Amino acid sequence: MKIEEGKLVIWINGDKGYNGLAEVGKKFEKDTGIKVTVEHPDKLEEKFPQVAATGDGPDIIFWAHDRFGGYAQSGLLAEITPDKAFQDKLYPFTWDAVRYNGKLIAYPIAVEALSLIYNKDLLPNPPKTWEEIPALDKELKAKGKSALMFNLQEPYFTWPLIAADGGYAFKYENGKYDIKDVGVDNAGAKAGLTFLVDLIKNKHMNADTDYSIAEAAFNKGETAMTINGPWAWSNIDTSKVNYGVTVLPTFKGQPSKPFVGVLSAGIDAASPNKELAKEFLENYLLTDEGLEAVNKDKPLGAVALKSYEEELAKDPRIAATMENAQKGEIMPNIPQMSAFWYAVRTAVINAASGRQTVDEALKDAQTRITVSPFGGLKRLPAGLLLGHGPIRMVLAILAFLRFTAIKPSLGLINRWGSVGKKEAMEIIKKFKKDLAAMLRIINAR
Amino acid sequence: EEGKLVIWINGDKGYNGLAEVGKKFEKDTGIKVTVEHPDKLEEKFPQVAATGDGPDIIFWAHDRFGGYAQSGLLAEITPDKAFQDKLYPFTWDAVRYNGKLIAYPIAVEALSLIYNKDLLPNPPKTWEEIPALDKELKAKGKSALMFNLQEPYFTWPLIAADGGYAFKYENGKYDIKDVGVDNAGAKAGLTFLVDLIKNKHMNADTDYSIAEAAFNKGETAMTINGPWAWSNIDTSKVNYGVTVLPTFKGQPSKPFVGVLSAGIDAASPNKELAKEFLENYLLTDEGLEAVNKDKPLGAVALKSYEEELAKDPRIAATMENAQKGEIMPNIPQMSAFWYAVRTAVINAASGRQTVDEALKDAQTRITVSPFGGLKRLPAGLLLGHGPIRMVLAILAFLRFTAIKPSLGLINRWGSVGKKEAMEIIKKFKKDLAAMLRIINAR
Ligand SMILES: OC[C@H]1O[C@H](O[C@H]2[C@H](O)[C@@H](O)[C@@H](O)O[C@@H]2CO)[C@H](O)[C@@H](O)[C@@H]1O
Ligand SMILES: OC[C@H]1O[C@H](O[C@H]2[C@H](O)[C@@H](O)[C@@H](O)O[C@@H]2CO)[C@H](O)[C@@H](O)[C@@H]1O
């Protein structure tokens, strides 16, 4: 939504406790008279880099830390410099997750990892291994039930199994990720995705199953197990299903390795409410009371705030969450992560639907990820400098030529003379908007 | 501002007489007409065009307008058939570019040999006479010849005499690949000029102001200048004659002929005002007379008044030297030509370069000038290599067109110095604003 000075607009995912966040925003307005609006737009992580620094986006964006590296590379995030006093209140490993090229670029909020969730009434002792689940499903099927439903549309949920036997995103040693060494192709990844695919083939799961379908099934008591994060516990509580939260099953004796996200709050680089945002984040949200308000709505997991984390550590569900976290890996925050997640999402969906073989799917994913950094434009359109092409491109290259004090061709200046007054004026105004965004990003540094 | 008129014209021309017709315009229209004469106005204009910091009307030799037009800085002019017949057809030609009229022709101007009758009763008819002439005058405490050596315009008539030429003219087009700055003719003309200097007949530092002061005080017998110069000379009370330029190897001195022209900025909100001013106030008998009465224009483009003044012997001399020379080309490449020859002449004059050095340098420099427009991006730009301004510009292009930049390019964006990038981008925004003012004025 359109940002004004003297107000705060926040984006969070629709699965997070946005209503509880709205409540701490209410206390903020009570004290400051500054209105806080919380929104949960669809595809906000894709949306943000598109509207950032223009004024059409939020002042504050919430998301797992993995996407913030790409934002920062674009310069879309304000640098966070909290006082050492505040920085001490949060676990250091959580600040690590939001540090990019020597700069802190967001506030860590909570650590989230997937767990195995099970119906204690249907399944008193959940399976310790993935390999046991087919026999278990056959057993539950005879009673009109299902062994396991979790959404297969999002790579976040299937990745833990794919990584169990040796799959990895980017090779990590010391403090660096090797963008040339991707592990989506290897034997471990294939074995993990193959087991998943066989699950579907043998009718133990359906390839179409998404978040909504899996949640409803578990919450209605139709399935004995699901895989989900702390945010899901609220709805399960409401359905009164007697459930347990535990360690994910092993694959080939090895733990499922979930990617660990740190839910983090970023401040838009061009925001005129930067001081406002930092006050809200530091002094209202990242407190025992602010976190409890959000956690009350939808559980955060293990909060980054030492004070409240120790208080919530007692909960067995959170201990299970943290146990899975230790067995998994903190997500890298590098820009290539976007390419990784996109390529792997395609591979899992294609393999699961029998659309491609496992080997075909993963080879494609690996190639797509390995080559992504080498992308970008390499040549201008053949006749752009001659004045050939869409009017938008032509006015853009004329702008380029003027910026660099270089004389345009005759074919190009003819287009400039021939363009309609209304057409050129709308196209340019957009350019003005782009230039203004660029200046705001540089100025915020 | 809207409802005001700002005009630029060279400072040695009749800007005061021009301001007079402007007060006339203000009397009948209520719109104030401001006249300014910035130094290097012909170089400054493309810098300030469409920004709001420049003039509504710019006066200059037709020479420079082909370049202005190519950058879209000029408004197309479309006078009636009635007004067009008022001016000589050959002057409308000089202000034709890409099948469009881009300025109003005012007057035709060419250089002439001006001489002191008291010091030199019969002026030299050849150039080769001048050295010995200088010796004769030096014994009387005088000088033979002083004229501006800092501007290629004043030297060119000598350089072009023995076969030096700007751009070849075949058919109805100028051969952009055929430049004659390095040939034997150009060599002979400049070498002589240089030997003239090393033999202390002239000084390489001599500029417009110095030469004018010397002639008008009667310290030098000759100078080389345009019709605009006659006004100050009249006032100095020096008895002078305006005659044909000297010869060189029996061949005539070939001055480049200029048509003083008035042009309107593409972004002017007062274009309608400007056109009425130029057509109905300036380019009349009364308007031109007012200007010519300040500083002589030469042979004006208005048929009527040119006929009334083709009686003055000074204009007769002007036109006489004009026939011997050539009308300047108005192509965009003319800008690179003048700059290249300016350096070659200044360099040779100071012994900084030998003549062959200076001309070969200018020649290849004029032949490889990119007025034909950009054909390729610089090597490695899209890979993120090059000067920061260019890299920032291409990143802007990419954002404008929603195209993904390379990683090298993205790396330059994060690596750029803040103050440097900010000044470049603020500049970009002003450039974009100028483009919009041009469109908004249509
Ligand atoms: O899918 C719901 C769940 O996904 C998120 O994980 C993301 C990752 O963070 C994104 O950058 C993108 O790559 O897709 C992944 C899902 O495949 C969050 O970590 C989590 O909070 C959110 O609820
Ligand atoms: O000398 C280079 C210069 O020559 C011409 O400039 C003349 C101008 O045309 C005259 O009207 C008068 O102002 O004297 C000037 C030279 O001092 C060209 O018009 C100009 O573009 C070129 O650079």
Image: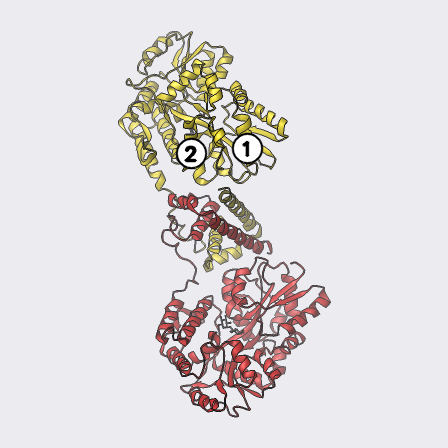
Chain colours: A yellow, B red
User: Do marks 1 and 2 share a chain?
Assistant: yes
**Residue A361 badge:** none
The residue nearer to you, when weighing B152 against B139, is B139
The residue nearer to you, when weighing A425 against B188, is B188
Is residue A43 among what the camera can see?
no
Mark sitting earlier along the chain (1/2): 2
* Identity of the residue furthest to the left in this view: A187
* Identity of the residue furthest to the front in this view: A85
**Neighbours of disc 2 within 10 Å: few (<14), some (14-19), many (20+):** many
Q: Secondary structure at mark 2?
A: strand
- From the image, tell me which residue sits under label 2: A99
Disc 1 Cβ-to-ligand 1 distance below 8 Å: no
Q: Percent from the top left, x then y, of residue A114?
A: 40, 20
Q: Percent from the top left, x then y, of residue A229?
A: 44, 20
Which quadrant of the figure contains the N terminus of chain A? top right
> Which amino acid is tagged 2?
Arg
Residue B312: quadrant of the picture: bottom right
**Residue A277 badge:** 1
Is residue A346 among what the camera can see?
yes
Question: Disc 1 to disc 2, how far (Cα)?
Answer: 19 Å
Q: Secondary structure at mark 1?
A: helix
Q: Which chain is disc 1 placed on? A: A
What's the residue at 42%, 28% (across, down)?
A: A92
Q: Percent from the top left, x then y, of residue A192?
A: 31, 23
